[PDB]
Length: 163
Image 1 (cartoon, helix red, strand yellow):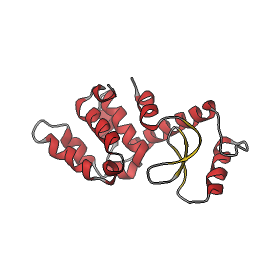
Image 2 (cartoon, one colour; image 1 turned 30 degrees about the horizontal axis):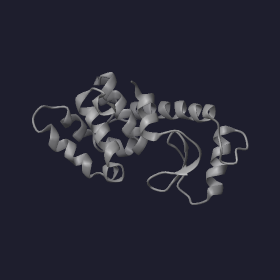
Image 3 (cartoon, helix red, strand yellow; image 1 turned 120 degrees about the vertical axis):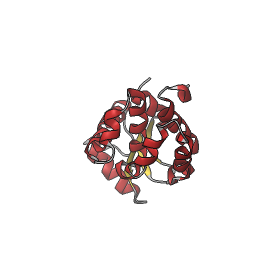
């Protein structure tokens, strides 16, 4: 498996505008449109990204294109961020993928604040206390099963959680 397969699972694929866990307007593979309650705003943002006049419905191909752009963005956010680049650089392909998923979901800022818990999770002594911290984030509380899966991946460096 890889990052793509991983998010497709966690995000699912949706061709009509939907609302995430925070009730925000979203489409395709976890592509957030806007934080406003203006469906029009969402639509407008959509047609913009897409080009065409979508009416809030896109194709699997369009969704997939947005998906590839979004994964690239996450990677760049990581590499531009002073706290995460070094972590990333040193990681193996599986823990890189977990880290990308976090950024994908919560943004570079959110993730960078946990840098120390991340590095701690990677030690042998009390690595679990570090895991616990993230459990408490607003993250986990919103999407607890996805948080476990991702954290498990990040700790183990295997795909067991996927399974």
